[PDB]
Length: 167
Image 1: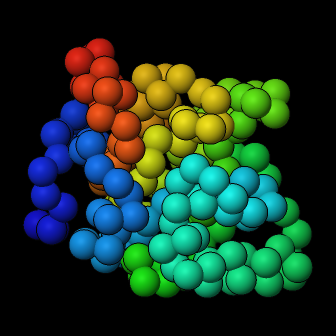
Image 2 (image 1 turned 120 degrees about the vertical axis):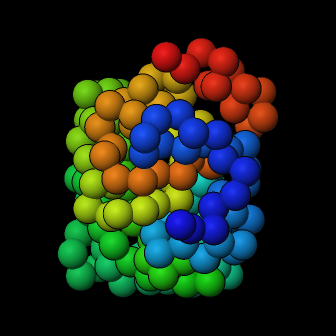
Image 3 (image 1 turned 135 degrees about the horizontal axis):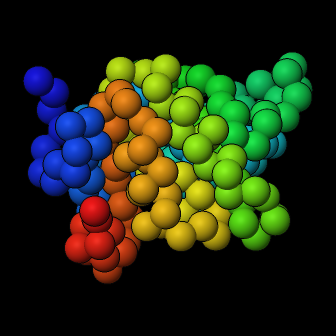
């Protein structure tokens, strides 16, 4: 049992809710919140900009030190950093950005990072400003993630379409 509330069950391990991931994280304080990161951990917009703002820029400060030490992530890769006031940990995962021409096959590799964590609160990878089709992202999530994932979908119209088209 966990405290995630109001989710629709899609499969044995995938759950979905129309919710603002920042507010969800503040309420639940999950062990892991996933960020829709880029390879430079520059949290400018989308989910990343929102999560970072909620940490009062502490996420960005930590991230800049991470990059200075380790260099950029890979597309499809991840790193675990602090969850600050949102979660115990933040799993920064880089899905491909279609607006950069990045190969959508890397979306599966990106979701594989979730399997290193028994429970996650997450957005749909590569959706939003990353340019991929969110229906496709949900399909890859369902077909790749085996651990328990609680998906927060920002946009209500999209949430309803994701549910109503789910196979």
